[PDB]
Amino acid sequence: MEMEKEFEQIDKSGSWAAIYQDIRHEASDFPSRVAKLPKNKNRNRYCDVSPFDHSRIKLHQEDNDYINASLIKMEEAQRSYILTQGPLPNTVGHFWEMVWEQKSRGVVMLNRVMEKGSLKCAQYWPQKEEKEMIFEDTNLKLTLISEDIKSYYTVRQLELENLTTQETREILHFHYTTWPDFGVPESPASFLNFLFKVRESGSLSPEHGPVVVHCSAGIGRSGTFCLADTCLLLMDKRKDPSSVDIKKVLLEMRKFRMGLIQTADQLRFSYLAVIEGAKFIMG
Ligand SMILES: CC(=O)NCCSSCCNC(=O)[C@H]1CC[C@@H](NC(=O)c2nccnc2C(=O)O)CC1
Ligand SMILES: [Mg+2]
């Protein structure tokens, strides 16, 4: 494929940092006024990772509608994603409120609760079935129904209950547990297989609200997940799969949330993920 030849070109010339800088310079810039508001300071994890106003998800409460989350709407691929930060101790209720209101079926987690000896994420789901979580601020109940631990990922069945109305929904929690503390994975095989597993569950399908994807900031590994999935979908859809430009898709995604793909090594990994992922469907 012509993407692999472009990949081999940048590899031989060692210009991954230069290509990544080009994207960084070309990337969209939009206001994040609501995010920067002083009352929303404790709702943000990082000062430099904000949702654009135009694509931000609004909570259905008149008090404070703010959550650090962006709707990425891919028109041509017919796919939507919510990218958000790993919830904070104070925003765990907000997080599940969004899952409920947006009618999400799947939650994709691409980090461990602890990485590099620091807390990257609040423990926002129950670890034992007998110990449910109740979120008093958003009036929601969350129960672990089942857990399936595998070598590279863990899938959890969760029940989310709106306590005001008593409706229940099954939420699928897809947790990629083997992303290395430093850098990117050596082989995209595990990541791609994880992707296919999320796909197979119907969590990315149009009959459901957009999947909720997060890592620490919801931009680095989260960007990779959405970029790979969209590129692969487009190669299936288009007349001429070679016309899929990963850089062009990324820049289109960057219109909805900042900083998707954080390093040149993450971009290289994305290429590899798309290249290897295509080879699984095209032999
Ligand atoms: C002032 C205030 O309120 N905020 C206080 C914190 S604001 S400064 C934080 C320091 N800057 C960073 O390194 C950011 C850069 C952007 C983002 N990077 C990643 O996505 C990432 N980080 C860690 C591990 N993996 C990744 C990955 O690539 O996915 C999160 C970390
Ligand atoms: Mg037990």
Image (cartoon, rainbow, N blue to C red):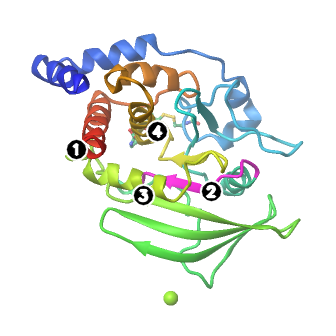
Q: Earlier in the sequence, mark 2 or mark 4?
A: 2
The quadrant holding residue 271 is top left
Q: Does 7 sit left or right of 174 as displayed?
A: left
Q: Earlier in the sequence, mark 4 or mark 3?
A: 3
Give the alpha-carbon distance from disc 4 to disc 3, as whole Å: 14 Å
Residue placed farthest to the left in the image? 12
Mark 4 residue type: Cys
Mark 1 residue type: Gly
Residue at figure coordinates x 53%, y 75% from the top left: 127
Question: Is residue 263 highlighted in magenta?
Answer: no
Q: Mark 2 points at which residue?
A: 105
User: Is label 1 in contact with label 2 (beta carbons under 8 Å)?
Assistant: no
- In the rendering, at what x and y percent does residue 179 appear? 32, 52
- In the rendering, at what x and y percent does residue 138 appear? 80, 58
Dot 4 lies on which element?
A: helix
Q: Residues within 10 Å of mark 1 (few under 14, many from 20)?
A: few
Residue at figure coordinates x 15%, y 18% from the top left: 9
Residue at figure coordinates x 32%, y 30% from the top left: 267
Dot 2 lies on which element?
A: loop
Mark 3 residue type: Lys
Mark 2 residue type: Arg
User: Is label 4 in contact with label 3 (beta carbons under 8 Å)?
Assistant: no
Q: What stretch is highlighted in magenta?
A: 101-111
Q: Which mark is residue 226?
A: 4
- Mark 1 vs mark 3, foreground winner is 1
Up the image or down, 219 lies above or below 153; here it is: above
